[PDB]
Length: 77
Length: 302
DNA sequence: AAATAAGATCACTACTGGGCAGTACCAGACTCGAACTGATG
Ligand SMILES: Nc1ncnc2c1ncn2[C@@H]1O[C@H](COP(=O)(O)OP(=O)(O)OP(=O)(O)O)[C@@H](O)[C@H]1O
Ligand SMILES: [Mg+2]
Image (cartoon, rainbow over all chains, first blue to last red; front, side, top):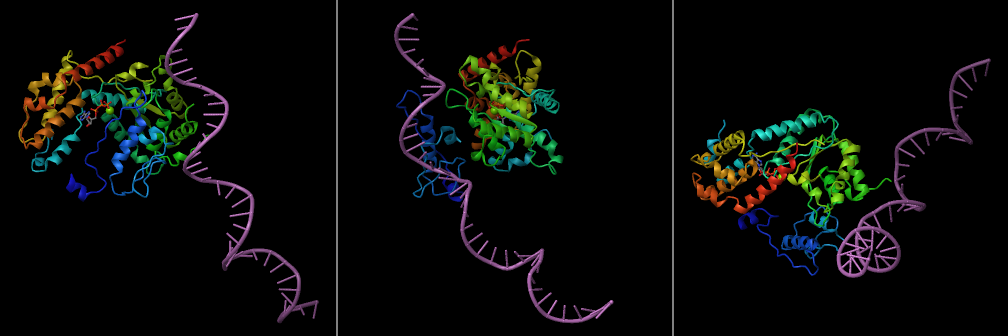
């Protein structure tokens, strides 16, 4: 997809994360959502995109930030 | 004509894949259920729930899309003057991450799909999310949708409580009572765990008419497959029914897999091994048949 | 029946949107003190 990535921006060919064994006794879906969002968006140029959630946005350094106040279905959206 | 255009052979393989992926066969069950649903929508008879069943792969979602398009084009002459009159709203239920279905998320997604502004600034003017609930009620009253489709309605039952399984639907019941909006809950056979009932039956092999219909849809699928040489498929109808159980939806994506594999190799026809490569697993069909048998037994009460 | 879970409630903590009583300006416009001036019995 590299020629297509060069031709068209805002495009990732493949994204991949690893599931995390939880410290508690139940799987953490909020951590899954936030880490998938970090992996998907952080290794990108500052392509201005507005997710439909108030808390999550980009920063000056480009690293994505998620407030601890953000509720998990909002992260999923 | 009844066959695929012969000009796509010179076109690139992506064009052939795009053409075949958009072909939606009108098998008799699909059009019969479509007519029943349209008759129910036109005259509701005072009902407010249009529960529709069917195991995965019958074609409920495409039926929803067809009904959406048909109702939009039916209303089209009268939205030129009347605005804020979205014909039909169709949403997909969210599988909860916790043990219980989330109703705040349902309300906010229903509001988003209606393009309702200022969702974050809602107010409660005197329950779960009263402000969002009242906002959705007002949006349904004023936008006046003909039907409110909720695909994947089986996720409403994620409550893990016998004394709360039926009560989980009180929010939708009250939202449909006081706004007068038809709620057509499309779901798999889990939805029978609980009003007009429609059954999206597959093609059971016991009845010869279903076998004839399955062979008909198989032939019309083979006619529209974009290959240089038309692949013979009706001979292995027994194989195509073993891994499909008679669902015209998963047959379509099975053929899509096989056709994409053929096109990627610049092939010209489909053999048995090509279908075997992209066939459903032996255990997968067993689990699917167990679930569909449970649903059929649940719906078998007369 | 005793033991082990689990939701409900109170209480405190940290975080982040975000508006109202109030001031200021700039000509356009209306209304009428005060006067000016001409016709008239
Ligand atoms: N009759 C049909 N003709 C052509 N394609 C179809 C048909 N029915 C379904 N599809 C295809 O199947 C996909 C949609 O899933 P499908 O309708 O088969 O499943 P469903 O059982 O209705 O849905 P779900 O399992 O999510 O409840 C799309 O790719 C659509 O093109
Ligand atoms: Mg579906």
